[PDB]
Amino acid sequence: HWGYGKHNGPEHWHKDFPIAKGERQSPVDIDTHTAKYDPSLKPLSVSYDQATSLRILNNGHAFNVEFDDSQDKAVLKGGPLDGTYRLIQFHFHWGSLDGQGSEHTVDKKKYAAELHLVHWNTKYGDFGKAVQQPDGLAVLGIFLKVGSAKPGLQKVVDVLDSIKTKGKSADFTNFDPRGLLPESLDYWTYPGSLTTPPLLECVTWIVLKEPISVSSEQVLKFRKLNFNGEGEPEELMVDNWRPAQPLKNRQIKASFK
Ligand SMILES: NS(=O)(=O)c1ccc(NC(=O)c2ccc([N+](=O)[O-])cc2Cl)cc1
Ligand SMILES: [Zn+2]
């Protein structure tokens, strides 16, 4: 099945998922000088005070942490969005080396990793229905650079030892994803897709300009995870990013000048 290798990786995904060559695929290179400053964009509202984290899951592609999204908690609104979008999960994409790992790039610059906070449009009732809609999801993307540690990341780093392998999960409550957010909520936004299969064109992307800093030690711990299941040959969970895709018709908007 699909993955990140030479024979099944991003260049192969179009065979099982033909939308891979569609008109609104993600990620993209963010050309900061062709992006349009839009003073009409309402500020972004990220309201995570009541986010109830539940569990962290290793799925064979990344580690997904899923939230209890059964109540009106942990919502993204404003910015380019109409209505309210509810947090369901976050995950990361990262590299084998500090010089790559991000999915979006900024004037061709690759960051060490990228965090995706995934939210579904509450007008569609749940995540599974929302992904079938053109405005179903809003993904908040945040770049990671290697420097000072991010203290709010450490609780995630420490649990990774227990989910080394595909299909392992651990209880993970009371985690404040506010600890993963940079100072500024300045952003770029554009219409796109999931960056893994099924590659559905259901996402309003909101990519923050300001990266967070994490330590080398923190990202090194991401790189100890495995793609393979327990009792299969060891293949380290690294370079789980899709490269930039063609922008095609699209415009990227900026919330700042
Ligand atoms: N990398 S990204 O664009 O943020 C992104 C990519 C893929 C997803 N996928 C999911 O959330 C997902 C999880 C489970 C299932 N399922 O039915 O088993 C389906 C999806 Cl679409 C979410 C976000
Ligand atoms: Zn992602």
Image (spheres, rainbow, N blue to C red):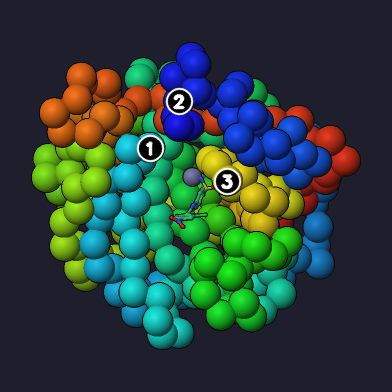
Q: Position of residue 20 (x, y in %)?
A: 68, 36
Give the structural element (helix, strand or loop) at label 1: loop
Q: Position of residue 88 (x, y in %)?
A: 43, 66
Mark 3 nearby-residue class (10 Å; few <14, some 14–19, many ≥20): some
The Cα–Cα distance between marks 3 and 1, rounded to whole angstroms, is 13 Å
Q: Quadrant of residue 74?
A: bottom left
Q: Quadrant of residue 104?
A: top right
- 107 in relation to 124, above or below: above
Give the structural element (helix, strand or loop) at label 2: loop
On residue 61, the disc is 1
Q: Is residue 139 left or right of residue 168?
A: right
Q: Quadrant of residue 204?
A: bottom right
Q: Report the residue at 59% width, 23% height from top.
A: 12
Q: Are marks 1 and 2 in contact (CB under 8 Å)?
A: yes
Give the structural element (helix, strand or loop) at label 3: loop
- 126 in relation to 246, above or below: below
Q: Is residue 241 left or right of residue 256?
A: left
Look at mark 2 in the image and give the residue it sits on. Answer: 4
Q: Residue furthest right?
A: 249
Q: Position of residue 97 (x, y in %)?
A: 36, 18
In this orientation, which residue lies closer to the viewer: 60 or 221? Answer: 60
The amino acid at mark 2 is Tyr
The Cα–Cα distance between marks 3 and 2, rounded to whole angstroms, is 14 Å
The Cα–Cα distance between marks 1 and 2, rounded to whole angstroms, is 8 Å
Question: Of callouts 3 and 1, which one flags the residue occurring earlier in the amino acid sequence?
Answer: 1
Q: Is residue 200 left or right of residue 50?
A: right
The answer to whether mark 3 is within 8 Å of ligand 1 is: yes
On residue 34, the disc is none
